[PDB]
Image 1 (cartoon, one colour):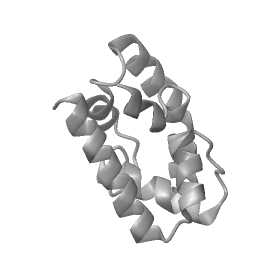
Image 2: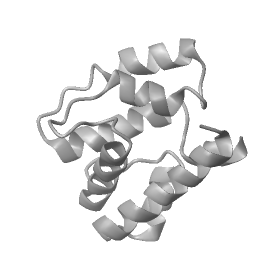
Image 3: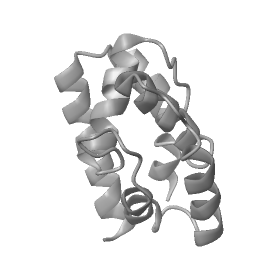
Image 4: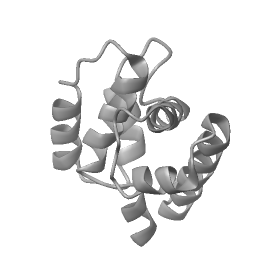
Length: 119
C-alpha cells in the first residue's frame, strides 16, 4: 500500500461515513483536523463508521492492535505505533459510539487525518 493509495482510501471512507451518518461537513472537517466533540452524536457515529471500515474496531467493539498497525504502518513509525496502541487500548467505554469518538481522539494526537494529506 502506497501513501497516495491510503490518502485516497482515507478520503473515500471520510466521504462514505459522512453520507452514512448525515454528519454536517463542518463537524466532519473538525474530526479530520483532530478536534473531536466526543459526545456529539453525529461525531461519534462518523468516528465509529471510520474505525469499523478500517477494521480498527471489530464487530464486537474491540480495539484492534493489528487493525491500527496495518493502517498506521505507512503513516507513523513502530515506536509511535506501540505508544499509540498502549495508550488507546486503555480506553474503556461501554457505549460503542462514545468509545469510537474517544478512540479517534486518542489516535488523532499521534496523527490527524488532515496531516495524512501532507505526506
